Image: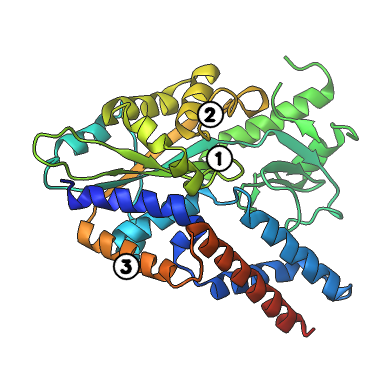
Amino acid sequence: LESPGFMVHKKLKSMSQSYGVMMTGVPAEVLGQMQAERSIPSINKTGNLKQQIAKEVSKVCHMMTEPTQSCGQASNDVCELLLGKIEAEKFHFTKYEALSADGDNLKNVLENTAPSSTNLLIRFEIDREDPPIVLVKTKNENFNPETAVKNKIYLLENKLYFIDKMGNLFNLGPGKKKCTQLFNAIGDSEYSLCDEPEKPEDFAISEIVDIFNEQKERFDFWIGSHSFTIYIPQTLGESPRQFYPYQAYFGSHTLQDWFVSDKDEYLSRIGIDKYIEKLAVLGKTTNTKERSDIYAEFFSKRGREAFFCAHLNEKRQPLRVKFKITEINPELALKNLQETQEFIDTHPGENPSDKVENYRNRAKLAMTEHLESLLDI
């Protein structure tokens, strides 16, 4: 006997293992048309249209068969199944809460809920602190704020700008005489913002770093790094409470790969408390080795834990762990899972893999035709 809440997990996992991308419930023709519209800006109207259409369809079709599911898309898919559209939107505008340094605030919410009578969905976001590291000196001409590389400081003859991660332009304060003074004290080669100054150039770069650091408050250097959810279904009786983490990782594995690999069950055995503690260590530590190892253990494709964050992929920047939590109505979630299953059942195909191939073919056809129509082929 399994609680309805657990059946939500069992059906979600099984369906994802079998049907992969069809999980979204988006009709193949809609998906293909969205891919076509996404490709349109890449197609130069002056050029060979038939050729570029064939190239864009091939790119997208390659990606269908590669791990190109973002972690946020997987989380949004889990939230919509379990919550339904209206409540998942509400959940999206709920504010994230920062995990306390030991994860007490999260554990407390779990201890304040009865394992028998509640079904919990937690959504996590991991941010990394990514301040600028390079100063670019440039003339006013050839400096265009719309096209310039984000997350850098730019020194002009008359201005000192910081473009942040969003491409927002921040004037850092100095007047024209201060900037023209700084412009001339530096040489001809981008320059580092991270390194006892001796050359007159070293003192001007050091000035710009001080100017920048004074107003750190104006800026947000944190950037989303990873996203995942955890589902904690209601238990039966005195059965111990169990969690399951769900995720995709763009470029490494999809949510289907996750579930096929059973890493959700593998991490589940760690226990929700020991899992929260390690998340808290991940956000609190200053140790790169410890940061990389926890990150790889929790978030890598199964079997790559030893090198996912090794060498160049070391997590050398401070991380931050945020969460939001809601309750789940299992019968609503089961209704949504069943509606998605009926959507899947309508695709021709004897095996799940046949239906996925049917879906992909239909998306490709729909993209080709929409791209031809839009470009008038």
Q: Nearer the viewer, mark 1 or mark 2?
A: 2
Precedes in sequence: disc 3 or disc 2: 3
User: Where residue 106 appears, x then y in whole percent?
Assistant: 26, 35
Q: Nearer the viewer, mark 3 or mark 2?
A: 2
Q: Quadrant of residue 334?
A: bottom left
How far is mark 3 from mark 2, CA to CA? 37 Å
Please say if 207 is above or below 335: above
Furthest-front residue in this view = 350
Q: Residue at x 49, y 64 (%)?
A: 350
Q: Residues within 10 Å of mark 1 (few under 14, many from 20)?
A: some
Give the residue type that dot 3 points to. Ile
User: Where residue 263 appears, x then y in whole percent?
Assistant: 43, 35
Residue 251 vs residue 183: left or right? left
Q: Residue at x 67, y 31 (%)?
A: 209
**Residue under circle 3?**
86
Q: Residues within 10 Å of mark 3 (few under 14, many from 20)?
A: few
Give the residue type that dot 2 points to. Gly
- Viewer-side residue, 55 vs 145: 55
User: Where residue 222 appears, x then y in whole percent?
Assistant: 52, 40
How far is mark 1 from mark 2, CA to CA? 32 Å
Q: Secondary structure at mark 2?
A: loop
**Residue 303 — which label?**
2
**Residue under circle 1?**
221
User: Where residue 307 appears, x then y in whole percent?
Assistant: 60, 25
Precedes in sequence: disc 1 or disc 2: 1
Q: Residues within 10 Å of mark 2 (few under 14, many from 20)?
A: few
- Viewer-side residue, 326 vs 156: 326
Precedes in sequence: disc 3 or disc 1: 3
**One can see residue 93 in this view:** no
Give the residue type that dot 1 points to. Phe
Please say if 255 is above or below 353: above
